[PDB]
Amino acid sequence: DGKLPFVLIPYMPVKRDMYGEPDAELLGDNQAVLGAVMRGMIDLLGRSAN
Amino acid sequence: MYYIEELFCRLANGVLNNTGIVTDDRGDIEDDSKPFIIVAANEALTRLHGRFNMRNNNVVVEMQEGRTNYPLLAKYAVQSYDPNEVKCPFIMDLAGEKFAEDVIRILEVYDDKGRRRPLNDRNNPCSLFTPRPNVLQNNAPKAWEVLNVMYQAKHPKLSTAEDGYNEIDIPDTLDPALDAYIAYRYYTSLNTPESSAKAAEYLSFYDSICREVVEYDLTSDTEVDTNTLFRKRGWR
């Protein structure tokens, strides 16, 4: 072949760049917000007398 | 903290300033009328320590074989028991901190091994029982079982005798409440209708002071703690 034996496969390509972006880049804030709501619901039920 | 003499001066130059039981110089109450104030003063202190959980004191009780009921009386204390009729005391105290039977309400009991003992739990075989407010009953006295009882305590009873207590240890914000109750007792004793109206004013004033303390929580009566049922219930 006469060149490097490595192959690059990006997931979401970046304009004029090698490394792509995974799905975790866009969902950073959404996961944190969702986690806060779930913990709040459990705390309301868990700490309540029953 | 201050001596009972300062209380006499404060009453002399206070609510009782216009009474016939004070000295000509308004410096002290009449000596023959002193026991009247002492009886009222002890009664007033009991009411304050009941509504407000100000003093929390603990005592040590040693289990004795063949005995189930353990009254919390000074005659069973090591520093005050009579060997003639008591084989051995089971209430342990110090020479300078003699037990004074100041028990009002039992709060919690812990054994010598650090395990909490339930009280008045009829369905629990190992629970303790209190047939009387100042009597502790154990249904299974072991060999080396020693119990510590933490309870709400009243102020020690005042006495004009030298060996007796002659100091007052209460929050200074409750001093007007103490004076009002003593004034109420004195004016209520007089049966003249004019004094009756004055007596009611002090009693109402005493109640107003107590609720004001509760409203602002000046004695740290309210208590909270971190939640533990969350872990025990397994919510995770």
Image (tube, helix red, strand yellow):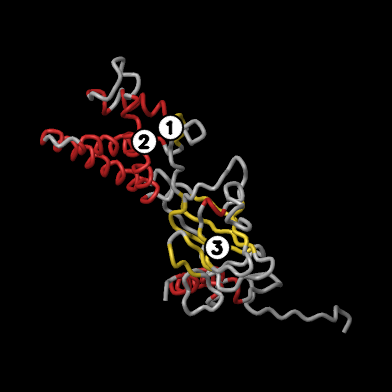
Do the dots labelled 2 and 3 sit on one chain?
Answer: yes
Spot occupied by residue B71 in the image (x, y as percentages of width and height): 51, 60
Do the dots labelled 1 and 3 sit on one chain?
Answer: yes
Residue lying at the far left of the rendered structure: B193
Do the dots labelled 1 and 2 sit on one chain?
Answer: yes
Q: Tell me if residue B155 comes above or below residue B117 in the rendering.
A: above
> Which quadrant would residue B125 be assigned to in this image?
bottom right
Q: Is residue B84 left or right of residue B103?
A: right
Query: Foreground mark, 1 or 3?
Result: 1
Q: What residue is at 42 percent from the left and 50 percent from the top? A: B53
Q: Are marks 1 and 2 in contact (CB under 8 Å)?
A: yes
Residue identified by numbered label 1:
B160
Q: Taking the image as drawn, is residue B6 in sight?
A: yes
Residue identified by numbered label 3:
B109
Q: Residues within 10 Å of mark 2 (few under 14, many from 20)?
A: some
Q: Residues within 10 Å of mark 1 (few under 14, many from 20)?
A: few
Identity of the amino acid at label 3? Val
Residue identified by numbered label 2:
B38
Identity of the amino acid at label 1? Thr
**Measured Cα–Cα span from mark 1 to mark 3:** 35 Å
Q: Earlier in the sequence, mark 1 or mark 2?
A: 2
Q: Secondary structure at mark 2?
A: helix
Q: Is residue B205 left or right of residue A18?
A: left
Identity of the amino acid at label 2? Ile
Spot occupied by residue B87 in the image (x, y as percentages of width and height): 62, 58
Pinpoint the chain carrying mark 2: B
Pinpoint the chain carrying mark 3: B
